[PDB]
């Protein structure tokens, strides 16, 4: 059963169970995989997405402790290109438009999120004590 | 190089980089280990230690995603006993008194914490924005 290289990219700010289940899903897309995780730069995240709490180094250091993560590209490019796929021998991109070309190419694998499991939601829990 | 069974127990509420580095350290105490993590019940934690945010199932589910964790006992007993060590074939208990008897027996391995890396500290960061 040949090894399949999966790439999942993202911010991974304040990593919670939702991220972890997505990473697990991507890791288990095939019997034998290498999961590469790409972690976005602080600047491109702020410019393109919004505020981020943790630094690149913090968000990357946390991901190193996750079981499903085989390799990390940090910082990663904001947009996936065909040359990037070729440079890293990537078979599929896992995420969940700017990946239409991956879908056209048969190189996109969708993964799902998990609601309520997040960090911001846990502070609410602490606060509901009042 | 024979396999060594390590047990680390704890609450593991709102798991952060400090926990993860402690788990990594315990996992890497010997060349070949099995790290068992014990997760304390909601009730005994509240009674003996203090408030806890996440439920037993949440705290346990998160730990399942950590690379260094080979096995989980959930809930675990609040106090480690000699019979418990025997039941699970545990060679060393990793933590950092109620483990004096483990030290007397040569079955205690100390691990260290990491300051500032924690969850409560990150909300401070968000708030310092004002």
Image (cartoon, coloured by chain):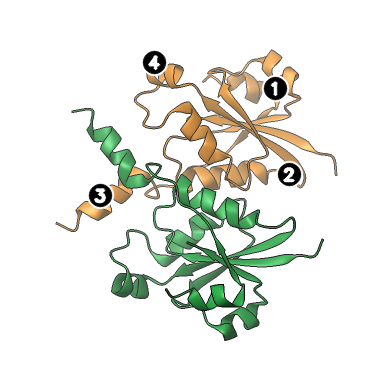
Chain colours: A orange, B green
Q: Nearer the viewer, residue A88 or B39?
A: B39
Mark before the other along the chain sequence, 2 or 1: 2
Residue A30 numbered tag? 2
Query: Which residue, as the protein is rendered here, is positioned at the far bottom?
Result: B83
Query: Which residue, as the protein is rendered here, is positioned at the far front?
Result: B104
Question: Dot 4 lies on which element?
Answer: helix
Please say if the residues under marks 2 and 3 sit with CB atoms less than 8 Å apart: no
Query: Which residue, as the protein is rendered here, is positioned at the far right?
Result: A1
Task: Provide the residue designation for mark 3.
Answer: A124
Task: Provide the residue designation for mark 4.
Answer: A47
Please tell me which residue is depicted at 56% across the width and 57% down the height of the picture.
Answer: B64
Asked if residue A63 can be seen in this view, the reply is yes
Question: Dot 3 lies on which element?
Answer: helix
Residue B33 in picture, x, y percent from top left: 70, 61
Q: Is residue B130 left or right of residue B113?
A: left
Label 3 marks which chain's residue?
A: A
Task: Provide the residue designation for mark 1.
Answer: A105
């Amino acid at each position: 059963s040949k090894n399949v290289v999966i790439y999942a990219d993202g911010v991974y700010d304040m990593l919670h169970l939702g991220h972890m289940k997505q990473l697990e899903q991507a890791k288990k897309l095939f019997e034998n995989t290498t999961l590469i995780v790409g972690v976005t730069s602080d600047n491109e995240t702020k410019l393109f997405k919004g505020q981020v709490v943790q630094t690149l180094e913090e968000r990357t250091e946390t991901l190193k402790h996750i079981r499903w993560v085989d390799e990390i590209i940090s910082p990663c490019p904001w947009v996936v290109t065909p040359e990037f796929l070729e440079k890293y021998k990537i078979d599929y991109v896992a995420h969940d438009d700017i990946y239409a070309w991956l879908k056209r190419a048969g190189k996109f694998k969708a993964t799902q999120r998990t609601e309520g499991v997040s960090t911001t939601d846990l502070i609410v829990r602490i606060l509901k004590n009042y």
